[PDB]
Image (cartoon, helix red, strand yellow):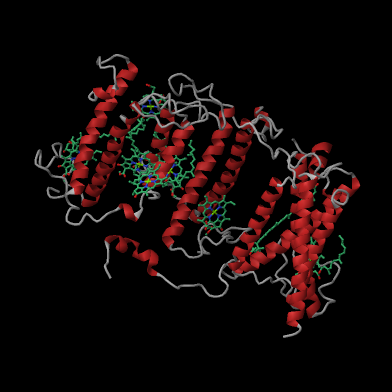
C-alpha cells in the first residue's frame, strides 16, 4: 500500500484509514512527511518541558511562586506573559532562518552532520528515522492529552496522578 | 556480526549505538562472554532474592549472626563480616577463572538438535533477569536510604503472597 | 526563581531576539544582492 | 628449567619437592607469574603493616568510620564495611586482569644491560618479603586471638625505636 | 644546535608547528562557550550589584568566624 515512506511498523502496519496517501501528489506526500517530522520534534520538546518545570514546582525547588496558583505549566500565561511572548518571538526568528535557508522538500535537514553523531551503516539509519517518527507521534498524543487534562481540572500532571489514586507516592 | 546467536524478534539486531561497528571476532567474543556471565549472575540473583523470603538455611554464617536473622535485600552486605564476604568472593573467582568445582562432565548434556535454540533461550532469559535485578536493587536501596519514597511496602513487591 | 531572575532571563531572551532579527535581516539582503 | 632466571649462590636451583619436573614451559611461565605477583604483593604488605603504626592518613573510609581509630593488621578488616572492601577488591582486579591504571608506558624503563639483573633482584626481594609477611601475620593473628601470647605485646617488634 | 638532554625530552611538544585544521574547525563550540561565559559574567555582576536578588544570597558582610 505505501509508496516507500520509511514509516509503517509491526504494531499496526500502514495506518491510513481516511485515504490521504492515495489522493495526494508526489510532492504532497513529501510535505505530509515533513509536517509529521516537525510536529513530532516540537511536541517531544514540549512534553519534556511540561514534565520538568511542573515537577520542579512539586518539589519546592524553584521557590514558592514558580507556577504560583496551581503549578500548571499553562499558568505562565498569567505569571510572566511577556517572557512567553519573547520566547515565541525568538523561536519565530530562528524558524524564519529555517524558512529562508532550507528549500522546499528539505525543511528537516539542519546540515548538522559533524556537529553530532549518526549511525554508520544504512539499515540502522532507516531504523533511526522510524524511531524519530514514532517518538514524535507519541509525543503529539501526549501533549494534546496534557493540555486538555490541565484545562479540564486545574491541577498538575503528577498531582492528578497522586490524587485519584493512580500512583503510590 | 549481524548473524550470530542473539538475533531474535522483535528487534532483529539491537546495536543502536554502534558498538559492533569496527571490531574483530575477539572483541565480540569478549562481549558475548560478558553478556552470558552477566545474565547467569542476574538470574541466580533474582532467585536468591525470592527464596530467602520463605526459607533460610539452618547454619550460622559468621561467628554469631546466624543465617535466620540477616536482612534480605541490599543489606546483608553490611551484616556479614567482611572476611567472610571476601572469602566467598575469592571462591566464586576460583570457580570463575580456574573453573574448578564448576566443570563436571555431567553438566554438559547432549542437547540433541536443539542446541542453538537453547543457547538463544538462555541468553534471552539472561537479558530479562538483568532488568529484573536492576528493578529489585533500585526498589530496595531507595526504600532503605529513605524508608518509603515509593509507597510500595515490602521487598518483593509483586508477589504479595509471601507477605513481603 | 524570584521576580528578578525571571526578569533577567527575559532580558536575555530580548537580547537574543534583537540579535536574531538583525541577523535575519542581514541574511535576507546579503543573499538577494550578491 | 635449571637455567631460567632465578638461580643465585645460596641454594642454586631450589626445587626440593620436585614441583617443577616434567612441567611444560607454559606452566613454568604461570608459576613465575604467580611468584612475581605474590612477591610484589608481599613487599607492599610488609610495608603496609609498618606505616600505620606511626601515621594514619586521615580520611573516612566509610560513612562513620575514620582511618584514625581502626586498629592495624588482621583487625582493620572487620572494621571497614564489606561493601567498601568489595569495591576495592574489584578495582584491584581491574588493574590486574584488564590492565588499567597500571600500564603507563613511561613506568616501564629500559634497563638495557641490566634487565637480567634487576629482575633477579626483584624476585629475590619478593622471596624474602613473602616470609616477612608470613611472620608478621603469625605474630599479628596469634596475638589478636589470645592477647599477650609470645609476650612481645607490640607489633613491629624488631623496630623498637618506632614504639610499635 | 646544542642538543641538550632536556631538549631531547621536550622536543615532541614543539615538534609540530603551523599545523591547522581546515574549514572552521570547532569554532561554533567556541561561540557557545563564549556566550555561556557572558551569561555567567552578567549573572555574577548583577548579583554583586544587588540588581539580581536571589534567595539565600545577601551581599553583605557575614560572620564566617
Ligand atoms: C576474586 C574473585 C573473582 C575473580 C578472580 C574473577 C575473575 C573474572 N571475572 Mg568475575 N565475578 C566474581 C568474582 C571474581 N571474578 C563475583 C563474585 C561476581 C559476582 C557474581 C563476578 C561477576 C563477573 C561478571 C559479571 C563478569 C566477570 C568477569 C571476570 C573476568 C575478568 C573481569 C574481572 O574480574 O575484572 C573485574 C573488572 C571490573 C571493571 C570490575 C567491575 C566492577 C563492577 C562494575 C562494580 C562492582 C560492584 C561492587 C564492587 C561489587 C558488589 C557485589 C558483591 C558484594 C557481590 C575474570 C575471569 C567478566 C568476564 O568474564 O569477561 C568480561 C564479566 O563480565 N565476573
Ligand atoms: C499533523 C500530524 C500528522 C501528519 C501530517 C502525519 C502524516 C503521516 N502519517 Mg501520521 N501520525 C500522527 C500525526 C501525523 N501524521 C500521529 C499523532 C500519530 C499517532 C496516532 C500518527 C500515526 C501514524 C501511523 C501509525 C502511520 C502514519 C502514517 C503517516 C503518513 C501517511 C498518512 C498520510 O497521508 O498523512 C496522514 C496525516 C494527514 C493527511 C494530515 C493530518 C490528519 C488530520 C488533518 C488531523 C485531523 C484531526 C485529528 C484527528 C485530531 C486528533 C504521513 C506521512 C503512515 C505511514 O507511515 O505511511 C507510510 C502510518 O502507518 N501516522
Ligand atoms: C553488560 C551487559 C551486556 C553485554 C555485555 C551485552 C553484549 C551484547 N549484546 Mg546485549 N543486552 C543486554 C546487556 C548486555 N549485552 C540487555 C540488558 C539487553 C536487554 C535490553 C540486551 C539485549 C540485546 C539484544 C536484543 C541484542 C543484544 C546484542 C548484543 C551483542 C552485540 C551488541 C553489543 O553489545 O555491541 C553483544 C554481545 C545483539 C546480538 O545478539 O548481537 C549478535 C542483539 O541483537 N543484546
Ligand atoms: C579452610 C578454611 C578456614 C581455615 C576458614 C576459616 C574461617 N572462616 Mg571460612 N570459608 C571457607 C574455608 C575456610 N574458612 C570456605 C571454603 C568458604 C566458602 C566460600 C568459607 C566461607 C566463610 C564465611 C562466609 C565466613 C567464614 C569465616 C571464617 C572465620 C570464622 C571466624 C573466626 O575467626 O574463626 C575463620 C577464620 C567467617 C568470618 O570471616 O568471620 C570473621 C564468615 O563469615 N568462612
Ligand atoms: C561457590 C562454589 C561453587 C560455584 C560458584 C559453583 C558453580 C557452578 N557449578 Mg558447582 N559445585 C560446588 C561448588 C560451586 N559450584 C561444589 C562444592 C560441588 C560439589 C557438591 C559442586 C558440584 C557441581 C556439579 C555436579 C555440577 C556443578 C555445576 C556448576 C555450574 C552450574 C556452575 C559453574 C554444573 C556444571 C554441574 O553439573 N557443580
Ligand atoms: C607464591 C609462591 C611461590 C611460587 C608460585 C613460586 C614458584 C617458583 N619458584 Mg619460588 N620461592 C617462594 C615462593 C614461590 N615460588 C618463596 C617464598 C621463596 C623463598 C624461600 C622462593 C624461593 C625460590 C628459589 C630460591 C627458587 C624458586 C624457584 C621457583 C620456580 C621453580 C620452583 C617451583 O616452584 O616449581 C617457580 C617459578 C626456582 C627458580 O627460579 O628456578 C628457575 C629457585 O631456584 N623459588
Ligand atoms: C576482582 C578482583 C581480582 C581479579 C579479577 C583478579 C584476577 C586475577 N588474579 Mg588477583 N588479586 C586481587 C584481585 C583480583 N585478581 C587482589 C585484591 C589481590 C591481593 C593484592 C590479588 C593477588 C593475586 C596474586 C598473588 C595472584 C593473583 C592472580 C590472579 C589471576 C588468576 C587468579 C585465579 O586463579 O583466581 C583466584 C584463585 C584462587 C585459588 C584464590 C586463592 C586465594 C588464596 C588461596 C587465599 C585467599 C584468602 C582470601 C581472604 C587473575 C588475572 C594469580 C596470577 O596472576 O597467576 C596465577 C596470582 O598468583 N592475584
Ligand atoms: C587503587 C588501584 C591501583 C592499583 C592496584 C595500581 C597498581 C599499579 N600502578 Mg597505579 N594508579 C592508580 C591506581 C592503582 N594503581 C590511580 C588511581 C592512578 C592515577 C593517579 C594511577 C597511576 C599510575 C601511574 C602513573 C603508574 C602506575 C603504576 C602502577 C603499577 C606499579 C601497579 C600495577 C606504574 C606502572 C605507573 O607508572 N599507576
Ligand atoms: C545537536 C547536534 O549537533 O546533534 C544532535 C542531533 C540530534 C538528532 C538532534 C540528537 C538527538 C536526538 C534527540 C534530541 C532525541 C530526543 C528525543 C526525545 C526528547 C523524545 C521524547 C519523547 C517523549 C515522549 C514520547 C513523551 C511521552 C509521554 C507520554 C507518553 C505520556 O503519557 C505523558 C503523560 O502526560 C500524559 C499524556 C498523561 C499524563 O496524565 C501522564 C503522563 C505525564 C505520563 C543529538 C543526539 O542530541 C545530537
Ligand atoms: C596489607 C594488608 C593486608 C594484607 C595483605 C596481604 C595481601 C598479604 C599477603 C600475604 C602473602 C601474599 C603471603 C604469601 C606467602 C607465600 C609464601 C610464604 C610462599 C612460600 C614458598 C616457600 C616458602 C617455598 C617454596 C619452595 O621451597 C619449596 C617448598 C620447594 C622448592 O622446590 C620450590 C620452592 C622454592 C618454591 C590485609 C591483611 C588484607 C589487611 C591489612 O590491614 C592490610
Q: Quadrant of residue B15?
A: bottom right
Q: Nearer the viewer, residue E35 or B162?
A: E35
Residue A28 is left or right of residue D28, and the answer is right
Q: Nearer the viewer, residue A28 or A5?
A: A28
Q: Quadrant of residue A95?
A: bottom right
Q: Where is residue B37 drawn, in percent x and y?
A: 47, 47
* Quarter that holds the C terminus of chain E: top right
**Outermost residue to the bottom:** C34
Please report the residue visible at 27 percent of the width from the left and 66 percent of the height from the top. E3
Instruction: Give ligand 5's quarter of the image.
Output: top left
Please report the residue visible at 85 percent of the width from the left and 55 percent of the height from the top. A82
* Quarter that holds the N terminus of chain E: bottom left
Q: Where is residue A118 drawn, in percent x and y?
A: 60, 66
- For the image shown, how many numbered marks are present on the structure? 0
Q: Nearer the viewer, residue A113 or D96?
A: A113
Q: Determine whether A76 is above or below D43 in the image.
A: below
Please report the residue visible at 78 percent of the width from the left and 65 percent of the height from the top. C18
Q: Where is residue A112 drawn, in percent x and y?
A: 64, 69
Q: Where is residue A115 drawn, in percent x and y?
A: 61, 66
Q: Quadrant of residue A55?
A: top right
Q: Determine whether B33 is above or below D156 in the image.
A: below
Question: Is residue A156 something that shows in the picture?
Answer: yes
Residue D95 is left or right of residue B66, and the answer is left
Q: Nearer the viewer, residue B107 or C19?
A: C19
Q: Determine whether E12 is above or below E40 in the image.
A: below
Residue D109 is left or right of residue B12, and the answer is left
Question: Is residue A138 something that shows in the picture?
Answer: no
Amino acid at each position: 500500500a505505501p509508496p516507500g515512506l520509511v514509516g509503517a511498523l509491526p504494531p499496526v502496519g500502514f495506518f491510513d484509514p481516511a485515504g490521504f496517501a492515495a489522493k495526494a501528489s508526489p510532492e504532497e506526500l513529501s510535505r505530509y512527511r515533513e509536517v509529521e517530522i516537525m510536529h513530532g520534534r516540537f511536541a517531544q520538546l514540549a512534553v519534556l518541558g511540561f514534565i520538568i518545570p511542573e515537577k520542579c514546582a512539586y518539589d519546592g525547588s524553584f521557590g514558592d511562586d514558580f507556577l504560583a496558583p496551581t503549578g500548571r505549566a499553562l499558568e505562565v500565561f498569567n505569571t510572566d506573559p511577556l517572557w512567553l511572548g519573547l520566547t515565541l518571538a525568538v523561536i519565530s526568528a530562528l524558524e524564519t532562518v529555517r524558512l529562508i535557508e532550507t528549500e522546499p522538500g528539505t525543511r528537516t535537514d539542519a546540515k548538522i552532520e559533524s556537529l553530532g553523531w549518526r549511525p554508520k551503516t544504512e539499515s540502522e539509519y532507516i531504523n533511526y528515522q522510524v524511531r524519530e517518527l514514532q517518538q514524535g507521534r507519541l509525543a503529539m498524543l501526549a501533549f494534546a492529552g496534557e493540555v486538555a487534562q490541565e484545562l479540564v481540572n486545574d491541577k498538575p500532571l503528577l498531582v492528578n496522578l497522586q490524587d485519584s489514586g493512580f500512583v503510590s507516592w | 556480526f549481524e548473524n550470530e546467536l542473539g538475533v531474535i524478534a522483535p528487534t532483529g539486531f539491537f546495536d543502536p549505538l554502534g558498538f559492533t561497528q569496527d571490531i574483530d571476532q575477539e572483541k565480540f567474543d569478549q562481549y558475548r562472554t560478558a553478556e552470558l556471565k552477566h545474565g547467569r549472575v542476574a538470574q541466580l540473583a533474582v532467585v536468591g532474592y525470592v527464596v530467602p523470603e520463605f526459607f533460610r538455611w539452618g547454619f550460622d554464617i559468621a561467628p554469631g549472626i546466624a543465617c535466620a536473622d540477616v536482612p534480605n535485600g541490599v543489606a546483608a552486605i553490611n551484616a556479614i563480616p567482611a572476611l567472610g564476604w571476601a572469602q566467598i568472593i575469592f571462591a566464586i573467582g576460583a570457580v570463575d577463572v580456574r573453573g574448578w568445582f564448576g566443570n563436571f562432565d555431567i553438566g554438559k548434556p547432549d542437547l540433541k538438535g536443539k542446541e542453538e535454540e537453547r543457547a538463544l533461550q538462555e541468553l534471552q532469559h539472561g537479558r530479562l533477569a538483568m532488568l529484573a535485578i536492576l528493578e529489585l536493587l533500585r526498589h530496595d536501596s531507595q526504600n532503605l536510604v529513605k524508608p518509603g519514597f515509593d509507597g510500595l511496602d515490602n521487598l518483593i513487591t509483586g508477589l504479595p503472597f509471601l507477605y513481603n | 526563581m524570584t521576580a528578578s531572575l525571571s526578569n533577567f532571563i527575559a532580558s536575555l531572551i530580548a537580547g537574543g531576539v534583537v540579535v536574531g532579527v538583525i541577523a535575519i535581516a542581514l541574511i535576507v539582503i546579503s543573499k538577494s544582492d550578491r | 628449567f635449571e637455567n631460567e632466571l632465578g638461580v643465585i649462590a645460596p641454594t642454586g636451583f631450589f626445587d626440593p619437592l620436585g614441583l617443577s619436573k616434567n612441567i611444560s614451559k607454559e606452566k613454568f611461565d604461570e608459576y613465575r607469574t604467580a611468584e612475581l605477583k605474590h612477591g610484589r604483593a608481599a613487599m607492599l604488605a610488609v610495608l603496609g603493616y609498618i606505616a600505620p603504626e606511626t601515621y594514619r592518613f586521615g580520611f573516612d573510609i566509610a560513612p562513620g568510620v575514620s582511618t584514625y581509630d581502626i586498629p592495624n593488621g588482621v583487625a582493620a578488616i572487620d572494621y571497614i564495611p564489606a561493601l567498601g572492601w568489595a569495591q576495592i577488591i574489584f578495582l584491584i582486579g581491574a588493574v590486574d586482569y584488564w590492565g588499567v591504571l597500571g600500564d603507563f608506558s613511561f613506568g616501564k624503563p629500559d634497563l638495557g644491560d641490566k634487565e637480567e639483573e634487576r629482575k633477579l633482584q626483584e624476585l629475590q626481594h619478593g622471596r624474602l618479603a613473602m616470609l616477612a609477611f608470613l611472620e608478621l601475620l603469625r605474630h599479628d593473628s596469634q596475638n589478636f586471638v589470645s592477647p599477650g601470647f609470645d609476650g612481645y605485646d607490640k607489633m613491629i617488634t624488631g623496630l623498637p625505636f618506632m614504639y610499635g | 644546535a646544542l642538543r641538550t638532554r632536556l631538549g631531547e625530552i621536550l622536543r615532541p611538544l614543539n615538534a609540530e608547528y603551523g599545523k591547522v585544521a581546515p574549514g572552521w574547525g570547532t569554532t561554533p563550540i567556541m561561540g557557545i562557550v563564549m556566550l555561556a561565559f557572558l551569561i555567567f559574567l552578567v549573572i555574577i555582576l548583577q548579583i554583586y550589584n544587588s540588581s539580581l536578588i536571589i534567595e539565600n544570597v545577601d551581599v553583605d558582610w557575614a560572620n564566617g568566624i
